[PDB]
Length: 541
Ligand SMILES: Nc1ncnc2c1ncn2[C@@H]1O[C@H](COP(=O)(O)OP(=O)(O)OP(=O)(O)O)[C@@H](O)[C@H]1O
Ligand SMILES: [Mg+2]
Picture (tube, rainbow, N blue to C red):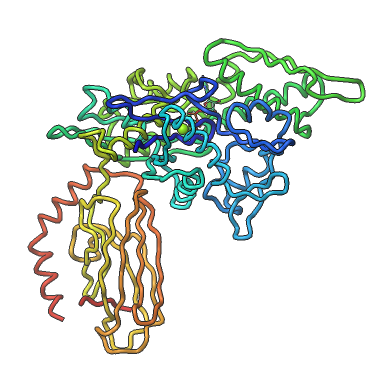
């Protein structure tokens, strides 16, 4: 029946639903509109999720899992996983297949199983509110997630007992939330998302034509090293160094103390968005031969700002790239939307307002907008939300090079995503044993006048006259905008494939120039294609 929207966060998760025309963020049993993304396995056999898991973490560092979003869909040898292994107090292991897993109480578990526990709590929160079963969900992911990260998030959804109707990017969700307000049509917005796990920036166009409001991503990127956990780490390091200076003890080899110090640091960081100073007070933090030792360290806001200044400044460069990739100036951004708990830091707000020259909108809730927008997309799919469309179309034609240096289109410009199209090709020479699939992007008919996106070989073709072998070429663009190209020899069974990342932006200024350029050269391109075609389309070596 109803489709719920779930923000599966590194730090916090949130669930929302469409209640007729207006979205509703749903409270859990303690009364909370967000739930810590924390899962704990206790000595007496319980599985805790949320605030109960958080409260017993500082005593159970081994069997309390958090920040599992940093692992999901990743390989054990991935750079980020290895960086994560040390800092995490729980055991991160390699699965038999090379995926990054965790081990708790001797049980080896895949991240989607762990995240499913958070998603089940979200589902139940919703089922409790509706008095009915819920099984359909829109789940969000960072815009930087790849296919494996998305698929694994879909898995966690299923393991939680959810039909995953849709995965959408978090900044897009926030834009749908904002785009519920009136007067927001025909605007460009910047979505500045500083969460617990990463920084993301997206430039999104909200247009309104013939009653339909459309949402289209013009640029995205970010940095997984600029999240609130990185802010926390700078303050932890300062608290470690200050305790060394005050009392000559290095807390880093004492896991229980470091766990208490991590939580205290985060709470102090949070408090310093409201106050000018705060006190970190941790009695019985450690002991040496002379008895127990106690921490009491005052931290001013200016000191915090000094500790994280470089982190905040490093968020500016991805903004500049995002605007370049959309072909826009700051003067084209009609509104700035802050998403994420870490944007509540006053220094972050001021730096963003300085860059854009305007104050971020204040009627967007940075903890809830992602979950709200996911619910909006849910209502779009059920038909409860009318006249709202997420627009994802190919900017330019996509194809391969064929004989004569021709670009042969498989997917035409302005095709809606996701999409899949196949065409069968053959060989250009008798007894040709291999073909080269050269993937091309653009509107020109000569392959060399278009952009090369990648290439690969298919060999093992059995000897046969030119034109006889059947090479099926498939272009599949998934919802993440990732292009999958395969080539399969139907008679030998051999197949080869590649994956082509989505572009970081859609620069309509440059796209329309390329379109006009092709139109200016249409006749020349037509004549070119014709007297080459006087020779089923064929592939050279
Ligand atoms: N008032 C505040 N001032 C500064 N930081 C805060 C404040 N409130 C929360 N935070 C920080 O916000 C971060 C979590 O924000 P949020 O809940 O948006 O993350 P998330 O959506 O779970 O993460 P991600 O988007 O990476 O998956 C944490 O690092 C937390 O310490
Ligand atoms: Mg988030």
